[PDB]
Image (tube, coloured by chain):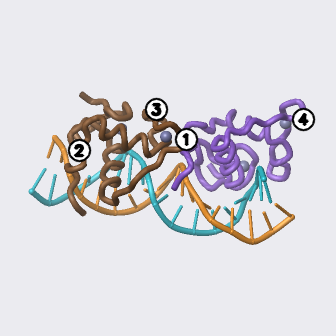
Chain colours: A purple, B brown, C cyan, D orange
Amino acid sequence: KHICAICGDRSSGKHYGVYSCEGCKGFFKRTVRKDLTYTCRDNKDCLIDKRQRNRCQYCRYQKCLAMGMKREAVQEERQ
Amino acid sequence: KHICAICGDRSSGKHYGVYSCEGCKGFFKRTVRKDLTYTCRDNKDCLIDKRQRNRCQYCRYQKCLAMGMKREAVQEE
DNA sequence: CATGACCTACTGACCTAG
DNA sequence: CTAGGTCAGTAGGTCATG
Ligand SMILES: [Zn+2]
Ligand SMILES: [Zn+2]
Ligand SMILES: [Zn+2]
Ligand SMILES: [Zn+2]
């Protein structure tokens, strides 16, 4: 309840279902808002930690969904 | 006689006429009090249920009025 | 130009006067 | 009964930095 279940950074609370950090939060939010398809240049299992979370987006996105981060809870843009 | 007619959630009775949950009741109370006008980013046809009632505020406010929810049943501050 | 560290609004479950 | 009310927790920001 104190760590980001995706990259191991300090959590700021539950976001879209799972305890995560501000970096992983905005990442998911930025993807579904714009509907972004990601390709992994590796074997679809790149490690995701605090230091190399931005190495492979694809696996960082998949790691969010395997941890239960809901696409549905991402509201639409405002104003 | 216990289902919210707007989003299918559990209903606590009549709120401004129509059977609705506390979430949709509070949303309608705040939409007239502040006179908030909404715009939709899609084709004004978003699905309104328990899981994405917070997705589009435009379609959620539209489904309220279409379900019979009355604007005059809201008292002033 | 995709990041993320800062910042507010908006929920809705849980209260009480008529 | 259905009108009111709050406020912690999760949503929405924006914008300088690489
Ligand atoms: Zn993270
Ligand atoms: Zn990868
Ligand atoms: Zn409802
Ligand atoms: Zn919409």
Label 3 lies in what chain? B
Label 4 lies in what chain? A
Q: Which residue is mark 4?
A: A41
What amino acid type is highlighted by mark number 2?
Answer: Lys
Q: Quadrant of the C terminus of chain B?
A: bottom left
Contact (CB < 8 A) between labels 3 and 4? no
Are labels 3 and 4 on one chain? Answer: no
Q: Secondary structure at mark 3?
A: loop
The residue shown at (68%, 35%) is A65
The residue shown at (42%, 40%) is B59
What amino acid type is highlighted by mark number 3?
Answer: Leu
Tell me which label, 3 or 2, sits earlier in the chain.
Answer: 3
| Label at residue B47 | 3
Q: Is mark 3 within 8 Å of ligand 4?
A: no
Q: Secondary structure at mark 1?
A: loop
Q: Secondary structure at mark 4?
A: loop
